[PDB]
Image: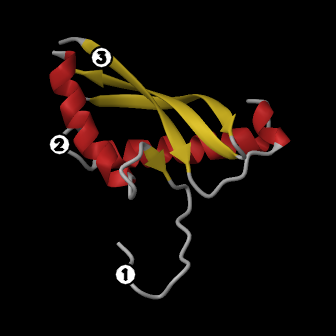
């Protein structure tokens, strides 16, 4: 078969960008990157792309505003447009606002289903 790479910039919800995030060598950077990679891996492992997904990795954490954005590369084995539409249906499971996002932790602020 053939290899395909996809990348996106995900808004990393509920995490303030701190200096430790400036360096890939820090505990903060590596643990957040590892959590994000585990989340993406788990989603594809539990999707229609389970046999095609190879692995993922955060290429870098960037600061946007005071929040964090993670540039992520995803590798698949298997048209790049076709693979893309399948991927989008999985990433949609990680989003709650329609944005390309990932929440290492979900904040609960009310007691009713706000959807």
Q: Does residue 51 appear in this view?
A: no
Q: Which residue is mark 2?
A: 48
Instruction: Look at mark 1 in the image and give the residue it sits on.
Output: 113
CA distance for labels 1 and 2? 28 Å
Q: Position of residue 51 (x, y in %)?
A: 21, 34
Q: How far apart are the two marked residues, 3 and 2, measured between alpha carbons?
A: 16 Å
* Marked residue nearer the N-terminal end (3 or 1): 3
Name the residue located 79 percent from the left edge and 30 percent from the top edge: 23
User: Is 50 situated above or below 39?
Assistant: above
User: In screen coordinates, is 98 left or right of 11?
Assistant: left
Q: Residues within 10 Å of mark 2 (few under 14, many from 20)?
A: some
Q: Is residue 16 left or right of residue 54?
A: right
Task: Give the structural element (helix, strand or loop) at label 3.
Answer: strand
Dot 3 and dot 1 residues touching (CB under 8 Å): no
In percent of width and height, residue 81 lies at 19, 21
Question: What residue would you read off at disc 3?
Answer: 4
Label placed on residue 61: none
Q: Nearer the viewer, mark 3 or mark 1?
A: 1
Q: Earlier in the sequence, mark 3 or mark 2?
A: 3
């Amino acid at each position: 078969k053939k290899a395909y790479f996809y990348h996106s910039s995900f808004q990393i919800l509920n995490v303030e960008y701190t200096e430790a995030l400036n360096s890939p060598a820090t505990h903060e950077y590596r643990t957040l990157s590892e959590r994000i990679e585990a989340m993406i891996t788990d989603e594809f492992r539990g999707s229609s792309l389970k046999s095609e997904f190879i692995r993922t990795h955060v290429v870098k954490l960037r600061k946007e505003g005071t929040g964090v954005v993670a540039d992520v590369v995803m590798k698949f084995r298997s048209n790049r447009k076709v693979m893309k539409t399948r991927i989008q249906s999985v990433l949609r499971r990680l989003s709650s606002s329609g944005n390309l996002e990932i929440a290492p932790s979900n904040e609960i602020t009310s007691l009713t289903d706000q959807d």
